[PDB]
Structures are given as C-alpha cells and as structure tokens.
Image (cartoon, rainbow, N blue to C red):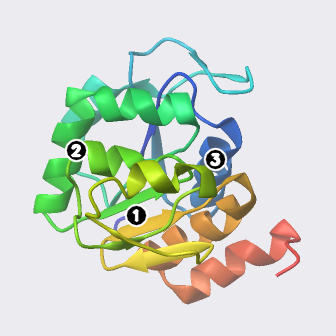
Amino acid sequence: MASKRALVILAKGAEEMETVIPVDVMRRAGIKVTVAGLAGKDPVQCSRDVVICPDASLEDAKKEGPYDVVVLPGGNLGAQNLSESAAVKEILKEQENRKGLIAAICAGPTALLAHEIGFGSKVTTHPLAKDKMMNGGHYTYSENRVEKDGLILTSRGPGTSFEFALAIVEALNGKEVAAQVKAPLVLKD
C-alpha cells in the first residue's frame, strides 16, 4: 500500500506556522509532502519574515499530481496570492472534480471562494476572515476550531494548526496513525 501524498501551496505572505505545522505533522504521519512554491522554486518570504525554500515550483509539482490532499495555508497576503492565481484555480478545480480532499486554514479558505470551490459547504476561517469568506452567502459559517464537510476541510488560525494537521492525517491515514503521531507532540489535548 503506497503512501498518501500532500501538496502544500506556499505563496509570499503565507503564515509560516500554518505552513510548517501541517508539513511537519503530515511527514510524521508518513505522508509524502511536497511544499510547492506558487511563484517558482525560489525562497518564499512568509508573513512574519521566516524564509522557506520550497521543494519544487507549483508548475513542476502539478505535473507530479494528483495528490490525496491539497493544503492551503493562511496569512492574509498569502491567501490573496493564492486567490489571484490561475494555477491554483486549476489545481483546486481538478482536485474537486476527482473528489479529492482540500484543506485550508485561517484566511486560506477565502481562496476557495475566489475559485468557486465547494460552494454549499459548512466552513470556518479565522474570525477576521469571516466577512470575506461569507460574501454572497455561498457557504455556511462554523465556529468549530476544525470543520470538515465531506472533502472540504477548514480551520481557524495558528492556534488550531495542530488540530487542522491531525485532522488531515486522520482523513488520509486513519485515527490510529493520527493518535500515534499526536502523542510525541506533547499537545495539551
């Protein structure tokens, strides 16, 4: 049984904690994760100036798809860049069409709105991104720290990143693996 694969799209202004926590946790779960740079293979300056080097450009990562999950980190500027990307729209449309999981956190879910992805789904976002996400009433809002409506998985912010990541792990590799990965993290609960 092959390992599941995850695509994490990294754009300038992305919230680095929301990027690194899921990448790290998913790799601990044995998931093959590809950190793809939206703008290319060059280093990406995140929201709080942490600079991360992507594994590959989104263009090249796309050719190695499809993935079991496409992950969209948050960060206002990062989400805006994801929202304006035609490449991202294509990847999300494809993932949605093949009934693959899409996970977005914080401001990240607003990219789903921009690309008309999963309308009708119950979703959550960072409290400050709620109004943007709800423009038009295409989704139903939730205040749950992690919300999962079928193949659309959303979360609220840096502080829900571990919960978000573990939810992705459970969705791809099961409850047992998620629990095994969780223990050594020393989370409160």
Res 140 visible: yes
Q: Is residue 160 above or below residue 18?
A: below
Tag 3's secondary structure?
A: helix
Q: CA distance from mark 3 to mark 1?
A: 23 Å
* Label 2 secondary element: loop
Q: Residue at x 47, y 65 (%)?
A: 154
Which of the two discs, 2 and 1, labels the residue nearer the N terminus?
1
How many residues crowd around disc 1 within 10 Å: few (fewer than 14), some, or many (20 or more)?
Answer: few
Residue occupied by mark 1: 3
Q: Position of residue 122 (x, y in %)?
A: 37, 75
Where residue 115 is drawn, which disc sits there?
A: 2
Residue type, mark 3 in image: Glu
**Residue 162 in the image: x percent, y percent?**
69, 64
Tell me if residue 65 can be seen: no
Reading the image, the residue beneath label 3 is 18
> The residue under label 1 is which amino acid type?
Ser
The percent position of residue 16, horizontal first and vertical second, equals 67, 36
Q: Is 114 above or below relative to 124?
A: above
Extreme residue toward the left, this view: 97
Q: Could you classify mark 3 by the number of other residues whose Cα lies within 10 Å: few (under 14), some (14-19), or many (20 or more)?
A: many
Graded by Cα atoms within 10 Å as few (under 14), some (14 to 19) or many (20 or more), the crowding at tag 2 reads: some
